[PDB]
Amino acid sequence: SGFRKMAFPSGKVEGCMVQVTCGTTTLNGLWLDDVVYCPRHVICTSEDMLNPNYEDLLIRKSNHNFLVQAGNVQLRVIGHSMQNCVLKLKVDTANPKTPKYKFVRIQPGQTFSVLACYNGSPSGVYQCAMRPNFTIKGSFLNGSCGSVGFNIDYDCVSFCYMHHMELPTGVHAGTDLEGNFYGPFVDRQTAQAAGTDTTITVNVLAWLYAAVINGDRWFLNRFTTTLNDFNLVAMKYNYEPLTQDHVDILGPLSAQTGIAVLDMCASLKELLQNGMNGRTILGSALLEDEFTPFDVVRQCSGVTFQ
Amino acid sequence: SGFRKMAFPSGKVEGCMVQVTCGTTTLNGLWLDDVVYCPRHVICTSEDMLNPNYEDLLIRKSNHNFLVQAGNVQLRVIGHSMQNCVLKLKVDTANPKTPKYKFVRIQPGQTFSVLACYNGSPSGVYQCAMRPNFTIKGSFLNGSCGSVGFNIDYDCVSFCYMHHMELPTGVHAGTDLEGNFYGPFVDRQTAQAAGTDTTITVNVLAWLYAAVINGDRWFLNRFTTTLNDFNLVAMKYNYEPLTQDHVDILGPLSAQTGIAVLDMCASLKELLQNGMNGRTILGSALLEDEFTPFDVVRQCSGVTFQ
Ligand SMILES: *[C@H](O)[C@H](C[C@@H]1CCNC1=O)NC(=O)[C@@H]1[C@@H]2[C@H](CN1C(=O)COc1ccc(Cl)cc1Cl)C2(C)C
Ligand SMILES: *[C@H](O)[C@H](C[C@@H]1CCNC1=O)NC(=O)[C@@H]1[C@@H]2[C@H](CN1C(=O)COc1ccc(Cl)cc1Cl)C2(C)C
Image 1 (cartoon, rainbow over the protein chains, first blue to last red):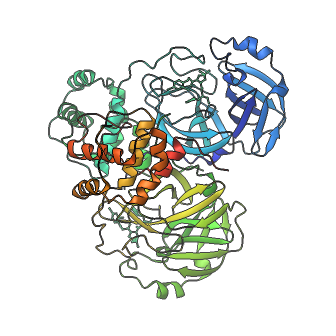
Image 2 (cartoon, chains in turn yellow, blue; image 1 turned 90 degrees about the vertical axis):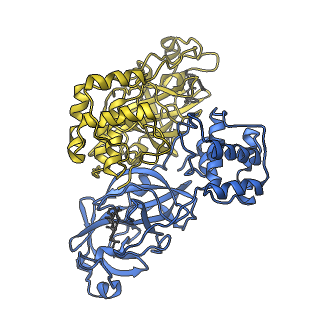
Image 3 (cartoon, rainbow over the protein chains, first blue to last red; image 1 turned 90 degrees about the horizontal axis):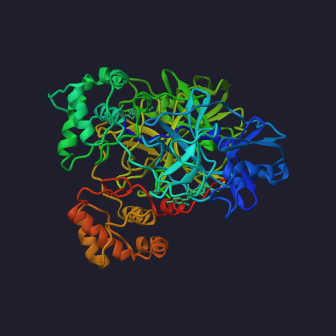
């Protein structure tokens, strides 16, 4: 037993990370087959990153302007092109470490592992959720652009995120691996802001089920509630509405614990109105919302990946 | 910016994990050079694990009783020996993936990354602290024994932990890689219990400095305190005593923020006596104690590993 914010093993992704330097900008790239993927603002400079015109900037570039460091070995760039907000640098060598992979775009509420990287070298790994406002609460410093987020499903890495920027509230924004931003953000230095977030209701319920599975039961009660009456409380506390599909997705957790989904909602209702009163749930004094039902089933059952 | 519970990249360790099966017990082993390391209770059975005599049990074993699966390839065991609570299985093949490594024993209060494994296959990675009572609050199910904890320091993996068991409170106990248990636990099924824990004071202060670096400042104050008067409050709230060396270790964080260590103690004192009053620190409603000063400096500065 026990319950931890757990990332996927990062080894398959570590073998794809490279360093991309252009001008005085160094960031990370993702090397799959004979392509290196990286944020397009690597082609920018100081006075560029204001309201840049990346098509103009890119046509002024040459293959040899892009220095690609795969560890202690330089990769020759033989072509370049822009795809939305990412660059695709064609290199003369296919990555012999290329795992089988997919480029997937995730939904707010879903989670993924981030391999934070600097100068092409992995620094750490942690779990993030896509917030309802399409930001992520990460840990990113200068030089971390091009770090990717991913999930693993048996032997296949599903890349879902490339890091591009921090917003003024300290949260982070980036793209899918096709270069399309999550949320209404642009890779310019403007006065853009996150905008209002909500709590991921279905995830909080999943985490409550994780707690019960692990022996935290004090928040349970004989009360129940209808979906509609629960959702008026959710709205009041800036929680996302709970749909019937969310109830369906929680079914296996409900069946394992023997606590009906709607009964757990009644428990969440009471926690929202009364707080916790000095008690904790799974070592937390806050209702946690960055674990999906899948995450709970995976950890409380022990799935692996080859 | 941002602050996350961050593990080390796990790739170097993933290449060492194997499956060890003996009788009807399957667990994980750690394959370094031509030795596989695993918990010695793999040689036990159901009626064995009560008050077993492992020397007697081991002399009754044969090299061929140990099935070692390195992925889809079987490793021939050519020798075996017991070292305290671990087995060393000599195999005919050296692991060509062996990273440079060390076997180190850590102190309570220090942190490490755990690569949770089942059937020799990595499942996830997360950060743990050695509690003052020599347990760890992990996430471990049946089959996870032999998963290791580790730190990475440039290119070198310092293995500090092998998993053996869960205690009745849901916390976890294991050994260093020389097979010596952390704390007063034995690899028998007895009525052993964790015993009383304390909060790691120096780590809480480090995390408060992490908060300030990341813009959470509401808990700061003009008050100060002496080390002695702080330590009477620490004792009252079941916090570990703060030593002058702890103050020294916090020096760089103090110097970066411009908040004297003893002034941050005064802030912790007030948080201990008043609570947080509905506010959070780094997304937590509890004082967090599983980040060392090193962890904070590493994350709030961006060190990597090759
Ligand atoms: C690429 O390595 C960086 C990663 C940034 C640096 C600090 N934290 C990060 O995640 N990306 C950028 O520097 C991008 C780049 C231009 C601006 N930018 C930003 O991150 C915006 O800036 C900030 C905004 C808010 C904060 Cl709290 C901090 C910073 Cl540095 C492009 C937008 C072109
Ligand atoms: C080896 O894979 C397991 C790992 C255990 C299983 C559940 N969680 C874990 O970390 N190790 C064991 O089964 C060891 C083994 C005998 C008993 N044992 C225990 O973990 C003790 O048991 C438990 C105690 C408390 C709880 Cl809450 C659950 C269990 Cl299963 C040796 C002590 C020989």
